[PDB]
Amino acid sequence: VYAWNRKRISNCVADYSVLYNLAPFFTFKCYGVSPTKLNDLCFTNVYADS
Amino acid sequence: PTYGVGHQPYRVVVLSFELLHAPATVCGPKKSTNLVKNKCVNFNFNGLK
Amino acid sequence: ALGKLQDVVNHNAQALNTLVKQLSSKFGAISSVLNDIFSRLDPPEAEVQ
Image 1 (tube, each protein chain N blue to C red):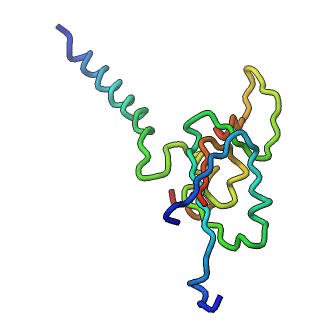
Image 2 (tube, chains in turn orange, blue, red; image 1 turned 120 degrees about the vertical axis):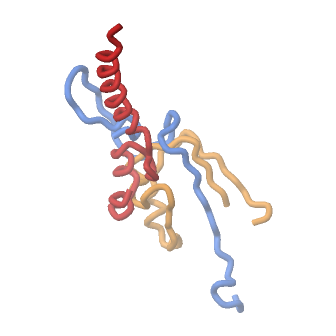
Image 3 (tube, chains in turn cyan, red, brown; image 1 turned 180 degrees about the vertical axis):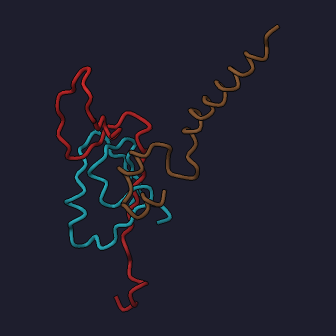
């Protein structure tokens, strides 16, 4: 955590179903957007942290 | 694993976004179609519904 | 010489044009466009905004 990792996602098509419906992801809570509105929208400047 | 839950390691991933305020690149599973000229329609335009 | 009539006309133009400018105020919402609010939120919070 002190030396965490960041990733830049660019030039892809977003499909959250494969990840929403996977077993280990028992927690999916979002802030600025509804959890089920992801597939209805386009994105730019997408980054992730691990 | 001898520690109780609440001490087990939990993998955390957070996602950052900017909403529509730039040319969108990453998109969802929507399928495009040809536009129209001078006809009253409704559009999506990368999210501008 | 006839600034009174111009005053009436200008007062109306300003009064109505402020109205057009009012739509650019979030009022403490996510944004000033209803469509985005409906297209990014679930009914409970969307309705609240």
